[PDB]
Image 1: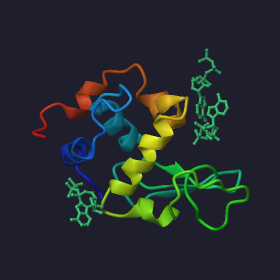
Image 2: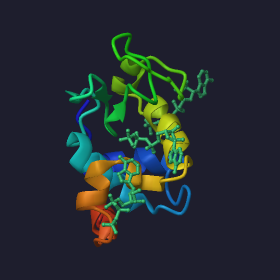
Image 3: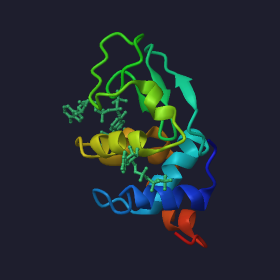
Amino acid sequence: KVFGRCELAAAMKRHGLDNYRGYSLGNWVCAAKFESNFNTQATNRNTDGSTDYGILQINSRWWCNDGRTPGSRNLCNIPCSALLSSDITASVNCAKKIVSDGNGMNAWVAWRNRCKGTDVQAWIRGCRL
Ligand SMILES: Nc1ncnc2c1ncn2[C@@H]1O[C@H](COP(=O)(O)OP(=O)(O)OP(=O)(O)O)[C@@H](O)[C@H]1O
Ligand SMILES: Nc1ncnc2c1ncn2[C@@H]1O[C@H](COP(=O)(O)OP(=O)(O)OP(=O)(O)O)[C@@H](O)[C@H]1O
Ligand SMILES: Nc1ncnc2c1ncn2[C@@H]1O[C@H](COP(=O)(O)OP(=O)(O)OP(=O)(O)O)[C@@H](O)[C@H]1O
């Protein structure tokens, strides 16, 4: 599923990401925009043999199991395929674990490089949530 911007904002808010660990909703929408272009099915392989999955590009070395990543830890205790669903629940639940882990949203490279410190509230402007 390719979400619209306000559609994803509303879904993320329904699933409890607004201000989760102090990160406002626009941070999460901005991260999804630049990680996956709002496409739940996005997958991208990394140099180390892991792959990133879903709307928030969660990686198979630490967070989910894809059966092909040496040293997989599966800290979200989920198959990576679950992070590709049209229903964002599994991605949200895993993202909540990631952002609680010490580095906050710096776990998402696209957030660090394209969202952090910017006017992220713009990502929810005009939306009826
Ligand atoms: N009665 C239920 N039976 C089974 N699962 C449930 C039930 N109520 C809630 N859930 C679980 O809640 C998870 C997420 O909540 P829910 O499906 O209600 O979100 P939503 O508001 O429809 O989401 P979105 O706004 O993204 O469409 C679902 O994956 C489902 O597993
Ligand atoms: N892949 C990553 N996963 C999680 N946190 C990360 C990752 N890469 C960087 N960070 C953290 O994000 C924050 C900023 O990252 P960055 O690499 O830019 O900072 P740094 O090397 O500590 O120095 P500076 O920000 O001063 O240039 C730091 O806390 C860094 O530890
Ligand atoms: N400062 C830290 N010291 C030790 N372990 C840490 C630290 N920060 C995070 N971790 C743990 O390291 C593992 C990877 O966390 P991290 O936030 O770096 O993940 P990631 O951004 O998805 O991966 P990567 O850094 O490989 O790109 C998790 O178990 C996290 O709990």
